[PDB]
Image (tube, coloured by chain):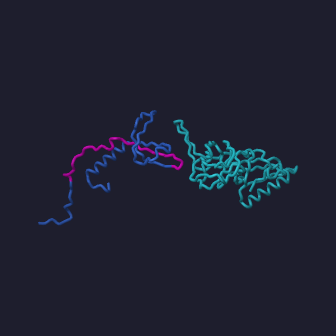
Amino acid sequence: MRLPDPYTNPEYPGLGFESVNLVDNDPMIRDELPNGKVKEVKISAQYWGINISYPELFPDEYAFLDSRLLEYKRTGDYLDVLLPQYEAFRVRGDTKSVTIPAGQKGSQIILNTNGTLTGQPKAGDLFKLSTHPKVYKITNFSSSGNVWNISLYPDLFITTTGSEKPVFNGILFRTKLMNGDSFGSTLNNNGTYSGISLSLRESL
Amino acid sequence: FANITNYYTARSYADRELKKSRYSRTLSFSVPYKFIGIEPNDPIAFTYERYGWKDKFFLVDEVENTRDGKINLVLQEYGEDVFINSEQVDNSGNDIPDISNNVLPP
């Protein structure tokens, strides 16, 4: 399920994201030895945290947003969040004729584009596999012919089976709405709803 | 001693315990994930320059392993003299058989 944004629903301009906050949550056990050497240990997973802020909402905008959020809380679905700043179209073509060799469980994807894709991905972009909902950021990219060497920040959450297909454009965050236990919005005497905030967390 | 019946072995063990009682001083500290494999009763040489310690002999007494790669240790001070055996004498002539509990013949 997609969170309402002024792409799908421009008739409600108040539903735009006044300010997004992409939080990097990678819990680690960091210990500082007296000999000046700082040591880290990583066990848990990394999850992208998204915080959405909203302006004053008119009754119709709030009605639409609240209906969507209640539909989410009813069906227990997953809110999809689209960040416009990450929607630069660089890689274009078909992602079905590209092959990803299997057995890749590290933090690096080696894929043979088979000359079917034009353009090259840029570092810091958003990358995602077609069979897993986790979202990756490209930290480095080296192309030697048709084989690409894409480096990802989160260690690969799945081991490639050879059937996965890279996804570069149209990437959505399969988030789950936090702070929904006590979710409310005050209605002022002037008819507009205020104090609406969405603390979302990537529940892959 | 319950399980010891040899007089000289029991005397040696008592001497060892008496020597070992003179080293009553314990030390506790934590080490990183490296040094993994420490177990109780292992020889460790401690060296803390602030004290007058340079390769001081210790034996592991308590070891605790955590899942976040930290090992808590408690060392027990020992000495070299604990394991050398002092000369003893023979008690061979001080045996007392129980020749009682029976009627002596005429």
Prevailing SS of the magenta stretch: loop
Query: What hue represents chain B?
Result: blue
Provide residue A54's location: percent of width, then percent of height.
Answer: 79, 47
> Residue at 41% of width from left, 40% of height from top?
B45
Q: Is residue A189 above or below residue B99?
A: above
Expressed as whole percent of the image width and height from the top left, the position of residue B25 reads: 42, 42
B44 w.r.t. A101: above or below:
above
Q: Is residue A76 left or right of residue A143?
A: right
| Residue B75, magenta (yes or no) | yes
Relative to A183, is B25 above or below? above
Taking depth in this image into account, of B9 and B38 the one nearest to the observer is B38
The answer to which image quadrant residue A1 occupies is: bottom right
Q: Is residue A137 left or right of residue A2?
A: left
Query: Was residue B63 drawn as part of the magenta stretch in this picture?
Result: no
Residue positioned 61% across, 52% down in the render: A100
Q: Residue at x 50, y 43 (%)?
A: B32
Residue A17 in the image, given as x and y percentages of width and height: 77, 47
Rendering coords of residue A124 (x, y %): 67, 42
Q: Colour of chain A?
A: cyan
Magenta span = B66-94
Quarter of the figure with residue A75: bottom right
> Which quadrant: the C terminus of chain A?
bottom right
Nearest to the observer: residue A6 or residue B52 = A6
